[PDB]
Image (cartoon, each protein chain N blue to C red):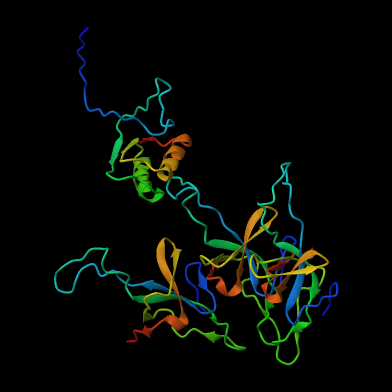
Length: 92
Length: 100
Length: 100
Length: 100
């Protein structure tokens, strides 16, 4: 049959990198409210470039989304680490 | 000169232990291990007798055991004692002393 | 020899603080940060005891704390004290003194 | 100075015997031979008379026969005595002494 689907908002066909950002205990979702956004054109390679954005997010105590060309294994290890212990709210 | 755990440097050397790794930041963020290099602040645990080159009497080392020091970046040998990495530098190479 | 904030150089060294960054020009224009390099005029804040190589007695450093000096281009190690970059040179390397 | 099996070093040298090969690990696993490199802990078996460079009187070697020492990584010559590899270093090159 025919279907009418009304998307509300914006959407792109690409998911989170590491399956540790899931804070939902539900159908495998990372779900935030009142989050920050970090838009990077080229890759986030090092620990150096990523730390200041996270210092902002933890200070203001809001989640943070990281939309970049990619999140390298070094900055990624920091993101997953800060996610799994005390519990900074991030996702890439 | 003074010794350490079954170890004693020779003539000029100084056995140090690098200080903490600085895993978290000051405010509230927290850091990995590939970054963060090797800490340059260390504590001296053994000291060699004295400079052999000093004519006649030996010139004893200046940094005394139990001090905190600012290490150089490069010069230094890795020694393993009781499965703890300690680093053996030369007395002339130690940059500063954290007196306080 | 004289110390600084919980820091003291060893035997020949000199801990200096580089002077301003020169952000604007003389007349009326204003400059970025990638240019302007590292300023060569600095102020000395700590001084090591004295040259160990001097036979018998140590030879004290000549540049005394509180002086302005013209640094060399290359020689120098970066030290961080209280989150302010200070640079540690050797006494023989310091070019000139701004006496006035 | 003291000798070893029909051998005697000259003026500064020190003949050591490298210690065990470390075939097995601490816990219970067991290792190959391409790995494990060359052991840096050795025992001194011959000692040369004394430093020729010392003006007038010779300055005798400091490491005395029968000591355990921390060898450097590179400096050293291979000698064959009774088909047992012994290594001949210079007295200044020996890093530490395992006093105990």
